[PDB]
Image (cartoon, rainbow, N blue to C red):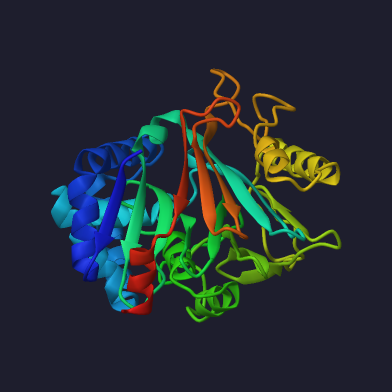
Length: 355
């Protein structure tokens, strides 16, 4: 997997990302455009105007992130609107049920160190577009995360021990001026604790669309299920565990409307809770949970099967909170394409201290 080290000003950070991942970003864009063009009544000219509006929101509200987005655009030799599109896919593609990703996520508090992880499931064509970034910003935690190339915030952890997971969620509502989900992910990745991540997401005063984010360290963790009109917090159960898939578990008002997750969202949730019931606590057993194939191909370790299942598990990440290490498996955990461990070095820590 391409690993890009980004440092300096927001623009310089974006430029390094765009330059180093130039060919990959071209593929990300072409795939995203194919995904949308196959489902909409609107012209490209109209859609470009929508992207212009979304870009202006980011420019006004989060200028540092917009500068990074401009940097990505310049380095990748693409239009700013194309990079905005990548970063607002959920919001931009609002109301296209075939365009949906999936996930299974879990946190377990344990006496020798908490474990947290997820599988992320989508079309296999995006797997080759997954990259990882190390971002150093003076006075902020250093961040290491896995993303589709061109996106500024996704799934990963930071030098302060904050680890973030993402699951698609399908509550109705779109607020074009609210915070985009991948912007919220970057906000969380820049925070020094889960408490701070919660506060800083709530500080934005409302979400643009619907998703679920889990934020955890060794000490505390929460999940957030949200729409533009609801932000509810999931907490550890009596067994010290959290499990989330792609449907609402929390008590949102009856005015909130869930838009048809797949039946397997429930099956995977029930299955993971069952597996955790018999889980012995070891890192080795934790890793194996993610390879579960009950209800294949719609299993926790999801498989492509033409005519049944369009997507597959494209990566797995496990955060070892005790050691501040993230183990990544590319592809399906049953037979990974590659495996590596991300760790922060003393230079990563020097940036975070502004030393």
